[PDB]
Image: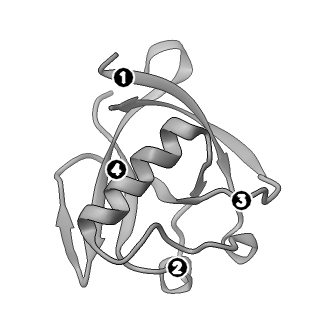
Amino acid sequence: KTHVQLSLPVLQVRDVLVRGFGDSVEEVLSEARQHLKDGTCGLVEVEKGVLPQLEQPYVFIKRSDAAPHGHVMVELVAELEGIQYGRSGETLGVLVPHVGEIPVAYRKVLLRK
């Protein structure tokens, strides 16, 4: 399917144990997509002071459209040293590996895969 319904655990930035997906734009987008497929991907809501506490390159989920079955349609955009790879809507958050951190909430998304 071109889209997959996912419920992403929302993590507090200070709980996150693995603060990025890798070392290149291509690797982080690759790893983000693999973790989303495997159910091992978390979401950190972006506020003042969050991104400097995570590792670049960043992978964002961004709104791709204006929400089937409560799932916001999203796509992946990576960022490295202020340049973004992809073009999309408003940021819903920054993706990170999930390795068992307790979430504060879930974000229902329809991921363009």
Numbered disc in front, either 1 or 3: 3
Asked which quadrant contains residue 101, the reply is bottom right
Badge 4 amino acid: Glu
Mark 4 burial class by Cα count in 10 Å: few <14, some 14-19, many 20+: few
User: Is 45 located above or below residue 73 in the figure?
Assistant: below
Q: Report how far apart the C-alphas of labels 1 and 2 lie in the structure.
A: 27 Å
The residue indicated by pointer 4 is 90
Residue ID at (75%, 72%): 15
User: Is 61 located above or below residue 84 in the figure?
Assistant: above
User: Is 74 located above or below residue 58 in the figure?
Assistant: above
Mark 3 burial class by Cα count in 10 Å: few <14, some 14-19, many 20+: few
Badge 2 amino acid: Leu
Label 4 residue SS = loop
Numbered disc in front, either 3 or 4: 3
| Residue 66 percent across, percent down from the top left | 33, 27
User: Is 23 located above or below residue 21 in the figure?
Assistant: below
The residue indicated by pointer 1 is 3
The residue indicated by pointer 2 is 54
Numbered disc in front, either 3 or 2: 3
| Residue 68 percent across, percent down from the top left | 45, 15
Residue reaching furthest right? Answer: 102
Badge 3 amino acid: Val
* Label whose residue precedes the other's in the sequence (2 or 4): 2
Numbered disc in front, either 2 or 4: 2
* Label whose residue precedes the other's in the sequence (3 or 2): 2
The residue indicated by pointer 3 is 99
- Direction from residue 22 to residue 96 in the image, left or right: right
Label 2 residue SS = loop
Badge 1 amino acid: His
